[PDB]
Amino acid sequence: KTFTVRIVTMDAEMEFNCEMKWKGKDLFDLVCRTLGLRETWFFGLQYTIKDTVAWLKMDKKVLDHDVSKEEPVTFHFLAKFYPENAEEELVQEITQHLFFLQVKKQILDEKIYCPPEASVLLASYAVQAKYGDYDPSVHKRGFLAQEELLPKRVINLYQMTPEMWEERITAWYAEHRGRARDEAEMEYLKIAQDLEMYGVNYFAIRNKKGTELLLGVDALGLHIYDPENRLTPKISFPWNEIRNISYSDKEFTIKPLDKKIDVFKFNSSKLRVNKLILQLCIGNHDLFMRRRK
Amino acid sequence: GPYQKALREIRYSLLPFANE
Image (tube, rainbow over all chains, first blue to last red):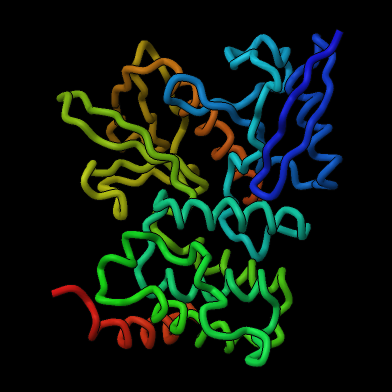
């Protein structure tokens, strides 16, 4: 027989009937062809188990994942990996879009820190993409009054009524005259991708001494943060500078390239988190090496 | 980068209304 599966993208939703023997590879390919997306390697189908995200493996049966079996079996089609340079690597317009949406959401949900002024400029572009050029005759007062525009963190740092923000944003919106949709979303991407937290996968760890720290994985390398400060890593290890990383019983070891360097060792208590880090390290490292050829 | 100036102009105009 078959089961139903729900695939949620940032944009939309879709349903599929799947044979009981279907693997990750089968769903993934199906979703990608539907989207007409060829740049598939930034993506993956994720689901959350316990409090940890999980990505469907290609060669395992879908149902052999510890995912809630209550039909429809739901997966989110999200980006697993970020390019080092959006404008250069996101060739297909559909790839651009999906990234844009997913990034804007992380900015509004405050998963990515974003200074007040950047939040405004971003908004003015998010607005241009959704609305097209600004027509003063068409776009009248309060035409943005029901729109998530800025992170809450930003709104309550100022003595400003929502209408004033919307006036600020409109002022910059007007400057984006003549800018096509994909032009705007990419402007958004170009700004957002310089945000210090953009594209960084955080994890709680602690070192040999047992003091609590944060691990950060992204397109550039592995990073170590003081739990209070996520903007600036205390230590960075670029991919080209790492021989490899080893995992062994809730312990990782970053084995640097220069034998000169001391190894870096840290601990994480959750197994599921650990597999995730390991996947993320491998894939980010791969893509990094691929760019360099 | 090329947004330095827009970011600065924006930051400067918000500054008067920042929380005490």
